[PDB]
Image: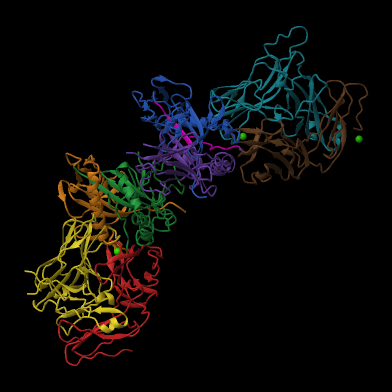
Chain colours: A blue, B brown, C cyan, D purple, E green, F orange, G red, H yellow
């Protein structure tokens, strides 16, 4: 029965310049769901969880609103000071062994993201792919930075190469991570 | 996701204890306040409570909260006639929800009754009429004649500056011929 | 504190009504309620901050705005008879603590326009019998013939509004389908009534039509006015 | 089952503000611990601990907020109770009927990579799990390495369990996996 | 206790010959298995197996040796007996009194090497061992890595169990170790 | 229950060009003992092991004499052929974590050796040390190659670098491995 | 590290069963053979055994091996007179170890006794003397004179080619004066 | 098979005796034993292969050699009286199977070199009573006057050696201290003895010194005196 679980119930992040917000829930490091600030609805990572539990979206919007307020207050008390950018780090790998021809998913791990503003896109040989590409919200790291995961379902082959492009402020030029079926 | 206030309207004699019950369903409400609105203007907060039964505030009011049953009520000990006001119970989490409201009316016993039906004259309009059934006990209820051209108001307590007085009142008037009163 | 703009307003079905609400606190949240008999307080809209705005219980028919963080305005596009009532504007902090309400606003909507008529106040002089028995005189102020129950009567004694010894009917009384009535009663010590120097006047503030009032033909135009009745002390 | 949330308190060129309420369960609903962090920019400044019973400013850039949030009984008492209305609440409610009771079969596949037998286990949602390497019936346990569970993100894990052993036709190595979903130890063989 | 050996049979620019008898025990003495190998150069050409019954040439370069030794009873019958006279004998003999019963205490120590908590466990003689990382009383199990038991060579082991968790002053990580010598789980802690 | 031990009882090796031989006994990959073909005595890796069990050394010399014979025959039956030399692989490390001042042992692993003829020595800074230098018999690899372990006890310091030079026919030039506490 | 053969010398009549016992101490011996050496020349292997009691070979001989007791013995059923030879039991691992040896002597069954003490004369020397006590039975023992000028040999069996013959013998001779052999029961 | 060289040898304490042993098998192992009465077979040396050589039970006093894989030679540096006995040379395979022994070798060591003397055989003729009774004749050979019991007497009938009908004492039978004795006996059918044509000889092989009692063979015949 000893030592287990750690839930985070109230992750609300907010950026001043662009007026960007993000409210989410996490259980044992996995995202339970994220309230969509615009569509005013609650999205659950695992669809089935929705059918079993719920959450008042408005509950997010408030914290995003108590957060947006504080942001400002703390901006005038520290007499307005910068936040040094940080170069992110990518890490590609498949979700399951590379069985030639068998439908798999490819995951791209980007860590140490700060601020939470990033453009992550995939590349097959060279072209940009759009379908099969999902992306999660921003997960919190204890060093108060964030990490994002981006998936890309594929079909394995000998005659192809996949890349994970990552654009951030911390980089004067994108750095795409390479990955081949080896 | 909505609260239930049962006693639509309530009436009790002075010094007695009034009980207004409420029941909700949602389970995120961590704040149950009560608002009283006097028949004159805007509503205001009276007493609130958070998870863990019992409330003292303004020793006369007490809130009984029962989480296990998701039921809570407001008790008013020694109910004065002035505490007559519409009562709204509420439940809050992200925002507030109110109930039907309870229109409380505390009847101030008239220690020295004196049922009278005075007739009022006016140098204004014509038919003075307008009988003023007053001072009568709060026990007796003011009837309502089904006659078309005849109106009768409700019992409204009047409070003066005298040592101790709180008489009732009841206006009545007509618009045609033989106006009499006398036995209303 | 908060303060609602039109504290009283009469409109025809199809009009563009707009209510304002100046707040004067460091509260971020602002809600616009709507009270009725049998239903009570119900939320229509609210905003967590300027530019923000969320629907509430019965947001249908309405559409509010929040231009500044100290002003939340409710807005009725196509007024309907089903929107007649009293609207309250509250201010408050997040996570629910205590909402501070506004004075109130009465709004009434009707198809035709003519029917609104000022009231016919008239003050009634006590019986000499009351003063001879218990030694108290009780005046009675009646008003009738008015439609929008936006009346607010008050007793004035020797040039001063008084509350200590008055009793009035909270709600304007019924009258078939058209026009409402209202009553009130001022009581005082005997000696004080049969005192010719003491002035007694019954006021009846009536909020009615203004400017935009294409009301031609005969009959006077019922504009917001204040009708009253008065009488002096006595001898006997 | 509705899950509550931590309710942030009001304060007294890119900028980032981050608020969060953390519930730490141990031994289940044995020992509960609630914490909230108001982090401005990238420096945590005010904080609340279920063990301190009050908001403490972790940095001097947050004294005002600390003192003021503890000067009001309404705000203080409310935060305090959050360990119940939130932590414990969600635990007995949402979680005990969603995340806690969710299992996931692990997909075991052996392969090679002058070589090293790699046994990759994948797609399972339980915390622990045990992977043992066996040779011809004999539990091998020397050249066995591990690569660290990797959180896939979509509620499943991935870990690699390697082994030295230079294979020699005739021997049958076997990857052994434990209760990441069932009580019938999964076994993957490999002769040849 | 005297230990007995395997006995190499006679055969009918650097060169290297090799012979070795192997006793594969399982469950202790439950199932025994004997095997010998005659290796020339680096090519094992002749072999015996506790499960085949007689010698079998693994390559054509050893057809002679294989046939002859299975013709003569004295040879064939002798070798088939070493399972008892060599394997079982030695086991119950010398081993069960020397290798087997020798325990060694582990020397667990935590340390650091943008950081990873390492928990080096050293100088123990039991193959098996369980090393578990714990946080503030909670059992962490995600960023946990391992480095393959390294045989020191003097009958002692050494292994390393990593952890990602970037440590934040205030927490207490603790390294947990299981019976590689005793029945009182050793526990190295690290505050700060 | 299940899965357990393995014992090689009777590892006999022998090289013809040099008349070199080696007899050893290993249990679970660890070396129980080895017989000394010159001094004609049994030698135990772990001395507290002889005081309990024993071995007739003569039983060793016999298998050397039997393998010597077979070497000879098997060289004639393959028409006399070489064996390609392999490139040994050193890997130095400590027996215990380095705790400045506290004596420690330093292990020089040397996998893939073939034939079993190699010179392993140590170097402190640059000078060759001789005290506290231990070495094991050849252990066997499932690919019929050999690996040897050479030890060196030392006193960890800030101002010194150790090295393990490996000499073998499969190397035209020795390749010492480098190790500093760093 | 040495074997023990007890019966230093043994004697039994024909057809009887002879038992020769051995006991060792070392525990690496996985080969226990038996060697017989006829009084004429070199020793040879007779029957051996490996761990697991009982041995048939040359149905007349049987080896009883008792690992639990580290004792083993050799049994000879229907012991003929020709199977008289020194018997060596051995134990082997790396090499062989032998025992004291057992000198077996199976006395023949003198069928029809006919004790006789003839005297042989020699066309060689002078004193004919030389008595040939013979044909007597194995029961009676051949005495030994304490006389310094008189030598007496031990009982020695003679085997002939005749249908059924196998008489004993004993030679006795002197080197001085009145020599007169003549005693028989 | 194997064959020991000096099958008989006499030496004085201090001499350098050398025994050889030619093997003729594909056996790698060769052992040199030493038999005595009361002790039996005891191993002195043995070799797993040419150039190899291991000590055995009582290796003291000796020092063997293994020049080829088909010849193992035992060597006595300083002979001593305690080395007198019979030496056997065996050949065999490893792991013990069956050791194939040699014919044997008798070696004797003394301080005094002379006491050695060839035997004085003397064949005794049958008893007429013997033939007159059971109908059987029994000649009786006898030898005495020799020190090294290296004798090997045999009967000979009509030019051939015989064994069917012979009974010789296993061991040479003493005499105070000096010289040994030995008595044999041959038995034949009456009708066969008293036949003037049959010849009966008693031979006594003797191995003595070399480079005066020396390897000879005393005999004492007699014909079938038909009487
Ligand atoms: Ca709710
Ligand atoms: Ca009545
Ligand atoms: Ca032994």
Using the image, determine if residue G136 lies above or below residue A43: below
**Magenta segment, principal secondary structure?**
loop
Quarter of the rendering occupied by the C terminus of chain D: top left
**Residue D134: in magenta span:** no
Residue H24 image point, x, y percent: 21, 56
Determine whether, in the image, residue C15 is placed left or right of residue D111. right
Q: Nearer the viewer, residue E167 or C104?
A: E167
Quadrant position of residue H122: bottom left
Q: Residue furthest bottom?
A: G178
Using the image, determine if residue F149 lies above or below residue G128: above
Residue C31 image point, x, y percent: 61, 28
Q: Nearer the viewer, residue D13 or A140?
A: A140
Q: Residue furthest left?
A: H211
Identify the magenta region: D2-19
Q: Residue furthest right?
A: B178
Residue C69 showing in the rendered view: yes
Ligand 3 occupies quarter: bottom left
Determine whether, in the image, residue A63 is placed left or right of residue F37. right
Q: Name the residue rendered at 70%, 28% in the picture.
A: C161
Residue E83 image point, x, y percent: 38, 56
């Amino acid at each position: 029965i000893e030592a287990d679980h750690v839930g985070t119930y109230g992750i609300s992040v907010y950026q001043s310049p662009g007026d960007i917000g993000q409210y989410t829930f996490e259980f044992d490091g996995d995202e339970l769901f994220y309230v969509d600030l615009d569509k005013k609805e609650t999205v659950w990572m695992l669809p089935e969880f929705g059918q079993l539990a719920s959450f008042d979206p408005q509950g997010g919007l408030q914290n995003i609103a108590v957060v947006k307020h504080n942001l400002g207050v703390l901006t005038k008390r520290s007499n307005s000071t910068p936040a040094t950018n940080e170069a992110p780090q990518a890490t590609v790998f498949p979700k399951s062994p590379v069985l030639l021809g068998q439908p798999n998913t490819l995951i791209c791990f980007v860590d140490n993201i700060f601020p939470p503003v990033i453009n992550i896109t995939w590349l097959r040989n060279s072209k940009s792919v759009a379908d099969g590409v999902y992306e999660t919200s921003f997960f919190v790291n204890r060093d108060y930075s964030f990490h994002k995961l981006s998936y890309l379902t594929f079909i394995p082959s000998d005659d192809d190469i996949y890349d994970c492009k990552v654009e951030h402020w911390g980089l004067e030029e994108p750095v795409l991570k390479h990955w081949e079926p080896e | 996701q909505q609260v239930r206030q049962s006693p639509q309207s309530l009436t009790v004699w002075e010094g007695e204890t009034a009980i207004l019950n409420c029941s909700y369903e949602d389970s995120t409400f961590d704040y149950f306040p009560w608002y009283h609105q006097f028949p004159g203007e805007s509503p205001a907060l009276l007493i609130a409570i958070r998870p863990v039964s019992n409330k003292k505030e303004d020793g006369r009011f007490t809130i009984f909260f029962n989480k296990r049953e998701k039921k809570f009520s407001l008790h008013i000990a020694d109910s004065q006639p002035g505490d007559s006001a519409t009562y709204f119970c509420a439940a809050s989490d992200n925002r507030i929800f109110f109930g039907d409201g309870t229109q409380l009316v505390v009847k101030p016993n008239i220690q020295n009754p004196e049922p009278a039906v005075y007739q009022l004259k006016d140098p204004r309009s014509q038919d003075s009429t307008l009988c003023l059934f007053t001072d009568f006990d709060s026990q007796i209820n003011v009837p309502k004649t089904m006659e078309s051209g005849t109106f009768i108001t409700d019992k409204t307590v009047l409070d003066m500056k005298a040592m101790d007085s709180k008489s009732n009142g009841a206006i009545a008037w007509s618009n045609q011929t033989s106006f009499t009163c006398q036995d209303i | 504190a908060v303060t609602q703009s039109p504290r009283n307003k009469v409109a025809v079905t199809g009009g563009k009504v707009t209510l304002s609400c100046n707040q004067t606190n460091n509260h971020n949240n602002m809600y616009w309620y709507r009270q009725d008999t049998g239903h009570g307080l119900r939320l229509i809209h609210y905003s967590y901050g300027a530019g923000s705005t969320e629907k509430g219980d019965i947001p249908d028919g309405y559409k509010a705005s929040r231009p500044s963080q100290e002003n939340f305005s409710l807005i009725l596009e196509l007024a309907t008879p089903s929107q007649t009532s009293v609207y309250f504007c509250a201010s408050g902090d997040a996570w629910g603590y205590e909402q501070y309400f506004g004075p109130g606003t009465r709004l009434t909507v009707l198809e035709d326009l003519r029917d609104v008529t000022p009231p016919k106040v008239s003050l009634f002089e006590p019986s000499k019998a009351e003063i001879a028995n218990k030694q108290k005189a009780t005046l009675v102020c009646l008003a009738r013939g008015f439609f929008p129950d936006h009346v607010e009567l008050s007793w004035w004694v020797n040039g001063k509004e008084v509350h200590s010894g008055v009793s009035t009917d909270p709600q304007a009384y019924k009258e078939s389908n058209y026009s409402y009535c209202l009553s009130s009663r001022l009581r005082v010590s005997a000696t004080f009534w049969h005192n010719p120097r003491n002035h007694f006047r019954c006021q009846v503030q009536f909020h009615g039509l203004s400017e935009e009032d294409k009301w031609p033909e005969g009959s006077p135009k019922p504009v917001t006015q204040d009708i009253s009745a008065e009488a002096w002390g006595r001898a006997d | 089952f509705e899950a509550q949330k931590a309710k942030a308190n009001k304060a007294v060129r890119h900028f980032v503000y981050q608020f969060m309420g953390e519930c730490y369960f141990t031994n289940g609903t044995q020992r509960i611990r609630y914490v909230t962090r108001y982090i401005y920019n990238r420096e945590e400044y005010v904080r609340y601990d279920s063990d301190v019973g009050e908001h403490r400013a972790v940095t001097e850039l947050g004294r005002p907020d600390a003192e003021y949030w503890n000067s009001q009984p309404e705000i203080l008492e409310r935060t305090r109770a959050e360990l119940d209305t939130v932590c414990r609440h969600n635990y007995e409610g949402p979680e005990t009927h969603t995340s806690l009771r969710r299992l996931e079969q692990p997909n075991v596949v052996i392969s090679l990579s002058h070589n090293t037998l790699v046994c990759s286990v994948t797609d399972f949602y339980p915390a622990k799990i045990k992977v043992r390497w066996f040779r011809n019936g004999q539990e091998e346990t020397v050249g066995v390495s591990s690569t660290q569970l990797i959180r896939n993100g979509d509620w499943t894990f991935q870990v690699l369990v390697m082994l030295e052993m230079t294979p020699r036709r005739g021997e049958v190595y076997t990857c052994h996996v434990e209760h990441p979903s069932l009580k019938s130890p999964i076994t993957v063989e490999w002769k040849a």
